[PDB]
Amino acid sequence: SMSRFAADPHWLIYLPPTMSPCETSKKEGMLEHPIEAFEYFRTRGVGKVVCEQKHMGSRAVVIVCKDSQVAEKRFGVLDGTAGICYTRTGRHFFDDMQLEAELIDRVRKVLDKSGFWGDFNTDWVCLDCELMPWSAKAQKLLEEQYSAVGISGRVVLDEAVKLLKQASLNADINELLQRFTERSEMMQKYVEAYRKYCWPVNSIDDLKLAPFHILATEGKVHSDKNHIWHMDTIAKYCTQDDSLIMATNHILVDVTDAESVDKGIKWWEDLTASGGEGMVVKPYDFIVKNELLQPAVKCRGREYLRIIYGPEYTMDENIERLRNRAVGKKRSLALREFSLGMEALERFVRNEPLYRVHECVFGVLALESEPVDPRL
Amino acid sequence: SMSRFAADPHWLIYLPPTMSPCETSKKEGMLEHPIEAFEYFRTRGVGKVVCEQKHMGSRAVVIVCKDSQVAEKRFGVLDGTAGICYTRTGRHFFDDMQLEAELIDRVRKVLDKSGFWGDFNTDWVCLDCELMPWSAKAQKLLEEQYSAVGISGRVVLDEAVKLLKQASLNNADINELLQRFTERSEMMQKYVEAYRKYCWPVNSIDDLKLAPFHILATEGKVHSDKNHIWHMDTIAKYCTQDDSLIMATNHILVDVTDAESVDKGIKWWEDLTASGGEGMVVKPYDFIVRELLQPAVKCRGREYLRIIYGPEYTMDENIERLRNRAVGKKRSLALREFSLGMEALERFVRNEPLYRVHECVFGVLALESEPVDPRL
Ligand SMILES: *P(=O)(O)OC[C@H]1O[C@@H](n2cnc3c(N)ncnc32)[C@H](O)[C@@H]1O
Ligand SMILES: *P(=O)(O)OC[C@H]1O[C@@H](n2cnc3c(N)ncnc32)[C@H](O)[C@@H]1O
Ligand SMILES: [Mg+2]
Ligand SMILES: [Mg+2]
């Protein structure tokens, strides 16, 4: 939203794919539960899956070059910058070129620290990340309103139960419910606004950056490495010594073994019940087969979904079946977009002409115009 | 229900005092919050308080003798037992003398291993503990019903908001949904009640968790001079060391006169309170002392209180006024009972005649008949 600057096309070597949850959990009062995501991957014979914490913010592709002379020779960028931080739609995340420049050099340092450039034999890197504008304004504004809906919501159930008992032996009650309605709808728009980055941050201290893929370095697309390699390699090479770049909370799960799977459901219920948005389940290996397999499945906590979905969180058999249809329509977009993204990277890495790279990149962008369920 | 054996009076050298929360919180939608308990102790010049996890179970006084002849020479007990585990009303916790005997010797062991008898120069010990009959019977039965009220409760709100947006464009099925939620909740109420009174006996000694928080007395000394960190630590070291049955308690020292510490405190409370814990018991760093000060204040989580209080968790100004009165009438019972307890111990320790000890002990028991608000 404040992401309003178009980016130099020379930087757009990749666009992130969309993602979908699993078919509506058949648990009562639940729309998404870890068991479906797990089932999905067992049935298609995967066995080991990685569960990563679904950071609540915006997706951000981050490219970092050693210097501005690298963005010239390697990317063809001429405006004298040495990196970029763009959203899922090819726009600069930040309406502020300096804040961005600061974030970039900030990562550049931690890489310099970890001698990353040498060990990967590369003078540049592309990272797939979640960026969270966790400014104080935001935190407070979100928490207090959640609190408000929580209070007003209970005050409803309490006064309503009373009203029942007393009539088993109508004025303020709707006012307490109308109140709850507003508090909730407001809470909806807040998360909406926050996730699209409509509330700009003042300083780089209000930012948390959580990389979860190391997409590419000089002469290689690391789509062969597994998602633990990613988690670990990332955590080591660019999480140390900076509060701004954070390692991600994860857990390896054996979807065959009901022992790892129960520890998994627990782990999910924990961070889901301590504020987390949810988790993204990924097949231990980056690209998975037999048909292509979703590169990730989003499993989101009840509390989060109750906000996003609104009163239509609870649904009947037919509105449910529709969600399952939508889940399908999205799973296909996800696959197509995912392949385009991958090919795009591949092409760029082997030094093909940029129009070839963009053939794929703008392909992802094209597909993103296709209609889907925003709630998915 | 299942603790109904009267105990040999020779074992009753102490009865535990009642406790009260702090005055009704002025935070919206909150009945009890860490800030009041903290304030209480600052307004009265304490400064350092200890916050202990309020284990959700039953209070149990546990006396452990080295052998059966120690119970003879020291306590006058003649039925050849070497320990006892009795409730706050002088009854045997267990309706099963062997289970109890098991529990006792279990503690006896972890003590020998630690060298407790030697270092305290004593061949017996009296412990103030929380006992939790966490059998599968109870965990499942509690969790699933809590889950049920959670589901059925959210479903009412959803279907009610929906119905509100409808009335603007112009059945009693909504009432039925509400009725369901009412039942689920009331049942959940009776479950916690039943569980906390120990109406659901346990299969194994493996279904038991024992959490000591005071070391009341050893040979020739009532340790009411040691501070509550001494207690926590000394207990954690001497009798929770290798056995799993007996557990050290989660605590945190708080400086009520510092923003940073009080805030870390409120956090610590919100964490475990929202991780299933019942709440915390706040204790003045030093056991005694000046004076007229509560030896402990209970601060209970919102989720817990909602169950216990029911629909009357939300109240008006008059009702709240009454709770504050009741909080007062209890604070006095607590003080009087607490002193009787302490004196009772003191007398027993300095070898006074038993009728002198029981003069105090039965005094605590007498006071417990005074009518109070059960929800406090
Ligand atoms: P969400 O409901 O926003 O849909 C998927 C998006 O989640 C974000 N995300 C957070 N954490 C991760 C990890 N660990 N891996 C992949 N994606 C993550 C991304 O921005 C997705 O677009
Ligand atoms: P609760 O609302 O049951 O009222 C006081 C009782 O709490 C129990 N309790 C749990 N944990 C503790 C600690 N750490 N210290 C003292 N009391 C505790 C006791 O059974 C009380 O009777
Ligand atoms: Mg870090
Ligand atoms: Mg232990």
Image (spheres, coloured by chain):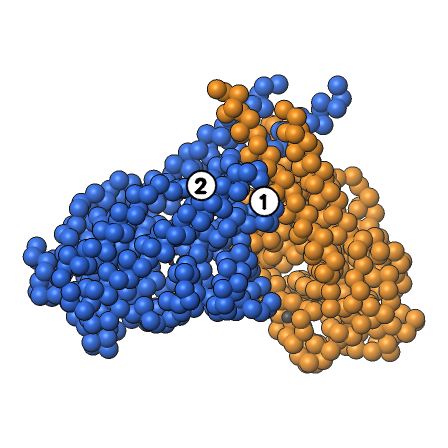
Chain colours: A orange, B blue
Q: CA distance from mark 2 to mark 1?
A: 15 Å
Q: Name the residue nearer the viewer: A9 or A6.
A: A6
Asked if residue A12 lies left or right of residue B71, the reply is: right
At horizontal 70% and vertical 44% (from top left) the residue drawn is A187
- Count of numbered badges drawn on the protein: 2
Q: Name the residue nearer the viewer: A249 or A40.
A: A249
Vertical arrangement, residue B27 with respect to residue B356, above or below: above
Check the picture and name the quadrant holding the C terminus of chain A: top right
Mark sitting earlier along the chain (2/1): 1
Q: Which residue is mark 2?
A: B308
Mark 2 and mark 1 on one chain: yes
Asked if residue A336 lies left or right of residue B88, the reply is: right
Asked if residue A5 lies left or right of residue B17, the reply is: right
User: Percent position (x, y) of residue A259?
Assistant: 42, 53
Q: Which residue is mark 1?
A: B29
Q: Residue furthest front?
A: B291
Pointer 1 chain: B
At horizontal 50% and vertical 25% (from top left) the residue drawn is A165
Q: Name the residue nearer the viewer: A281 or A141.
A: A141
At horizontal 45% and vertical 51% (from top left) the residue drawn is B21
User: Percent position (x, y) of residue A79?
Assistant: 92, 71
Ligand 3 visible in quadrant? bottom right
Q: Secondary structure at mark 2?
A: helix
The 10 Å Cα crowd at callout 2, few under 14, some 14 to 19, many 20 or more, is many
Q: Does residue B53 show up?
A: no
Please, what is the three-letter code of the amino acid marked with disc 1?
Gly
Which of the 4 quarters of the picture holds residue B238? bottom left
Vertical arrangement, residue A279 with respect to residue B154, above or below: below
